[PDB]
Amino acid sequence: KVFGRCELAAAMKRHGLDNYRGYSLGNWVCAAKFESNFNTQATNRNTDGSTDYGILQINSRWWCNDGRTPGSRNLCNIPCSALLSSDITASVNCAKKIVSDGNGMNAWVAWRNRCKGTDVQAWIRGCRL
Amino acid sequence: DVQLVESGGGSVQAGGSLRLSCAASGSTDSIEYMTWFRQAPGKAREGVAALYTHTGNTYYTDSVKGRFTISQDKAKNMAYLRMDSVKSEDTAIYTCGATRKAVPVRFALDQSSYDYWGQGTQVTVS
Ligand SMILES: [Cl-]
Ligand SMILES: [Cl-]
Ligand SMILES: [Cl-]
Ligand SMILES: [Cl-]
């Protein structure tokens, strides 16, 4: 499923992401845009045998278990398949753990590179939330 | 790929100070942590001090807390280890490590979390 911008903004708001760990809703919408282009089925293979899964590109070495990644820690205690669902819930609940790790949203490279320090509110503007 | 190069090191008197430097080059944009490890004679490598480059947050092994300070110059892709108040037990080969993955803090002092390594530099406390 490829979300629309405002569709995803409303979903993320319902999931309690607005101001989660201090990050306003726009940060999360922007992160999803640059991480996955709003695509819930996005995947990216990495050189360590891990894969990044889903709308927020959560990694299989540290966060979810895909059964094929060396050194798997599975800190979110979830199968990576659950992160490819059309509903965002499993991704969001894992993202809540990730953003709580100690370095905020810096865990998401695409967010650091294209969202951090920008006018992130633009991503929810017009959405009638 | 990322190249790491250490400078500094050598002899120091107990109670004294030494500064180590680590310069990163190559695919430096994706660097997440720069971290100092060490390996004392006859012992396994251990993480000493980790720095998360996008916030400046730092993580230390218990045996060095308060004595060693890791810092960076992010714009120049540098990490520094200031070793103050050195002890006998600090004699070791010190190695810079880096990674381009967003490693959870709890695993930031584990060597298996790191992808790139310097050459090692000897520090000897007399
Ligand atoms: Cl916002
Ligand atoms: Cl931040
Ligand atoms: Cl060279
Ligand atoms: Cl070492």
Image: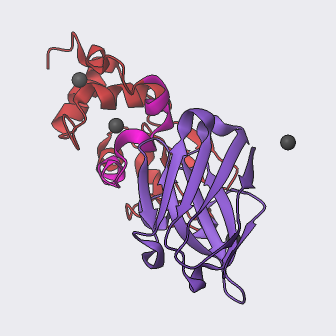
Chain colours: A red, B purple
Does the magenta-highlighted stretch encompass residue A103? yes
* Quarter of the image with the N terminus of chain B in it: top right
Q: Is B83 in front, or is B95?
A: B83
* Residue visible at 47% across and 52% down in the picture: A81
For residue A102, side relative to residue B110 (left or right): left
Residue A93 in the image: state x and y as whole percent.
29, 50
The part of the chain drawn in magenta is: A93-114
Q: Quadrant of ligand 2?
A: top left
Q: Quadrant of residue A107?
A: top left
Q: Quadrant of residue B41?
A: bottom right
* Quarter of the image with the C terminus of chain B in it: bottom right
Q: Main secondary structure of the magenta part?
A: helix
Residue A101 in the image: state x and y as whole percent.
35, 55
Q: Is B124 in front, or is B23?
A: B124
Q: Is residue B1 above or below residue A7?
A: below
Looking at the image, how many numbered discs can be counted on the residues?
A: 0
Q: Is A128 in front, or is A111?
A: A111
Residue A2: in sight, yes or no? no
* Residue visible at 46% across and 41% down in the picture: B54
Residue A66 in the image: state x and y as whole percent.
54, 59
Residue B77 in the image: state x and y as whole percent.
62, 39
Residue A89: in sight, yes or no? yes
View extreme (left): residue:
A129
* Residue visible at 19% across and 32% down in the picture: A13
* Residue visible at 45% across and 39% down in the picture: A108
